[PDB]
Every structure is written in structure tokens, then in C-alpha cells.
Length: 99
Length: 99
Image 1 (cartoon, each protein chain N blue to C red):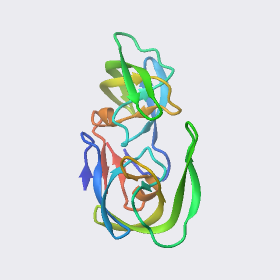
Image 2: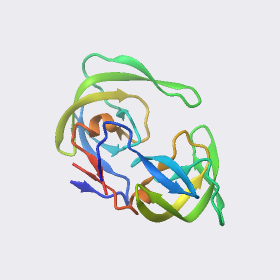
Image 3: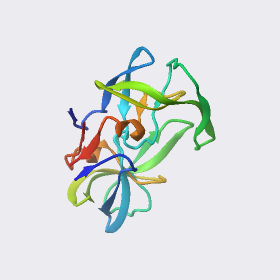
Image 4: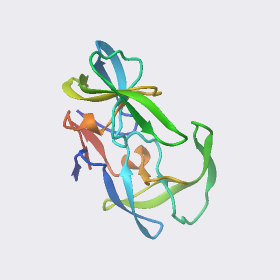
């Protein structure tokens, strides 16, 4: 699709056997979800850095469906007001900025 | 142009008589620059909200050239590690997400 930016670019996600929403965020390097229970191995990751760091769980090679596109990428699990699709997964669905 | 997302989408800016760089950030509602001296009227704006609020100067209808495109939009002036082009100005240059 082509998504204009007059509104926040929120899209539908299938992840961890659940239906979720997430923000397509070109300003984010990484992808973050809260309230998902992902299977398999994880390792801790420190992110943020302003005011302190936040410790999240890093899951590698997570299957995820983003707006109908079944792809694979790293997903961080930790607190976030809106789930975020970062560049690491936008590259996987072939998403570009165009003007 | 078409900008892929394997790297951070940094572009060249002309603003306030200066040459700057800024991040095209679809996760940001607003546009923020530091170290610019903009002419004309401004009003205070509270943004952020995590850990407290940050007070910035809001300048309306600022002429700004983004990657060769001369447009107009609100620019906030305050501290930011990288200058940010938010959705308010990406709409002005006709920028969309495509996949």
C-alpha cells in the first residue's frame, strides 16, 4: 500500500499468535512490543539511555506479519505506549519513503 | 527520491539561513531543531511528558527546504540529539510510506 502521513501510520500486526497494532516508525532502529508472549530463546538488551536505561528481552528471528506481509526480524519485548515497527522490520516488508 | 530504510533516513535541510541535517521520522508528530535562530513570533509549548515535560519554542509557518523541496510548517526549537522532521512537514513534501 501507499500510506500518507496526515495521521499516525498504525497498521495491523500478527505476532505471537495475537492480533496487535503498531506504529511504522522510521525514526526507530528497532521493533518493540509489550504484552506479547514470544516462544523460544531471548537475551537481555539495554535500550534507551535518557534518564537511565530500560532492560528488555531481545528475541531474534521472530516471525511476524505486518500489514499482510509475513516476514522475520528481531523483536524487543518491553514497555511501550504504542507498539513500534522500526527500520529493522520495515526493510523486510520492502517499505520505503517516497516523495 | 525513494529512500530505503537500511540506514537512518537523514536528509539535508535549509532552515533559518543555515545548512542542517535532519531525520525523517514517521513516528514523530512534530518537527524539532536545536541551534537555529528563527525570526518572527513564537510561543512556548510543552512536549514530551516522560519524566517531566520539556518546554520548547513553537514557530508557526516556518519556511524550510527539505531535500530540495521548499515548504512551510511549524518548527519547534529545543534540545534534540538529531534534528527531526516529523509528519507535520513530511506531508508538505508529499512523503509517503510505500510497500
